[PDB]
Amino acid sequence: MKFSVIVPTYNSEKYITELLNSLAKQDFPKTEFEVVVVDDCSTDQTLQIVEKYRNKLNLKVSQLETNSGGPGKPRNVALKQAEGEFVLFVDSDDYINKETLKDAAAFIDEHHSDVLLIKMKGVNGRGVPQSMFKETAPEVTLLNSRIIYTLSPTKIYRTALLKDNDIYFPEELKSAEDQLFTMKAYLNANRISVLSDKAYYYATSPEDFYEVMRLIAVEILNADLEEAHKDQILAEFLNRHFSFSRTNGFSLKVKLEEQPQWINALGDFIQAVPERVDALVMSKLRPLLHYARAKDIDNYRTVEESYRQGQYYRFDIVDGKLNIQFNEGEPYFEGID
Image (cartoon, rainbow, N blue to C red; front, side):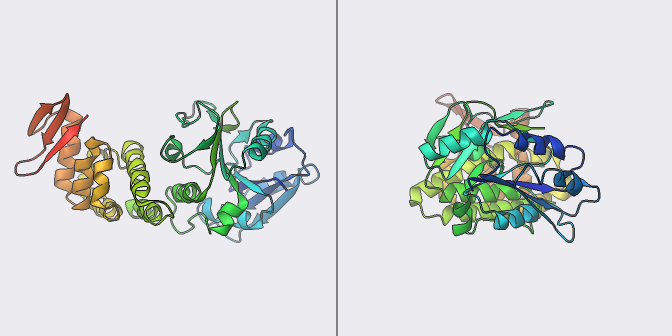
C-alpha cells in the first residue's frame, strides 16, 4: 500500500466522522491506503462510529487496555501495524483535503521524498505554522528553510525511514514528545520536501518538557552529519525554542517560588548544548543560554526583565546594536538586536 493514515483516538466521538469522511472523499483508491485507528481506551463509542467505515475504508482498529494519557503510545502501536509505504498522523479533531493523497502520491513518485510536509490551514481561528509553506519545494534542508519551526507529526513520513532508524514517539514523556519524533525524522531523511499547491491538513511541570529538549540536543549532536552542520541545526532549534516555546519569558510569568524548578530543568537541557553553539544563536539569546547553563535564575530573570522594560544596567550602542551588561560585575553581551 501507498499510505497509512494513523488516527489516535480518546473520546473522539464528537468529530471523528468529519475526519473519517475526508478519508472517504479521497480522490485516491481505498485499495492503496489504510486507516490505522488505535484507541486510547475511550469511554464513548468512537470505535463504533469508526466501525461504520470498515466496508468503505481499508481499516485497522486496536484499543489499548488502559489510557496511556497521550497520543504517543497510540501512534506507536499504529506505526508498528502499518503496512503502507508512507505514513500520515492525523488528529481525530481534524480533517484533510480530498486531493491530499492524490497530490502527495503524485509528488512522492516525482521526487522520492522521505519526509513530505503538506501545507496546513487553520479552521475556526486556529494558529498554524506558515513560514515554511509559502512555496512548493522538492528539496529543503534544516538550514535553508524553516521546517524546524514545525515539528508536529501532521506530515508524511516514509515508513521504513521511521522503522529502519527506530524513530518512535516518546511514551514516558508527555509534553512536546512529537518534537523529538519529527526532529529524528528530519535528521535521518535523505530528502525532505514541502508541498503547498493548496491547503491539505486542516487544523481545528518542566522536568518532562526539558527532558525532551535535552534529548533533541543529544539527537542533533550525535547525528551522522558534519560537525559544523550539527552545531548550526542545534542553533536554529534553540532560536525557535527560545522564541516560541514556554521557555520564552518564563521568569516573567512563572511564580517566583517555582522558578528554581524551571532553571534547574532548563539548565540540564542547556548543559547538553556546547558553549561554542551560543555564538551561532541569535545574539539576544546568548545571555539567556549563559545563565541557564549556570542555573542562575536571578541573573536570568534580570535579563528577561531588562529586555521587557528596556532598562539595562549598562549598555553601549555599536553598529546600531546593543552591547549590554545586565548586572554589576557580569560580562557584556554584544550585538543584541
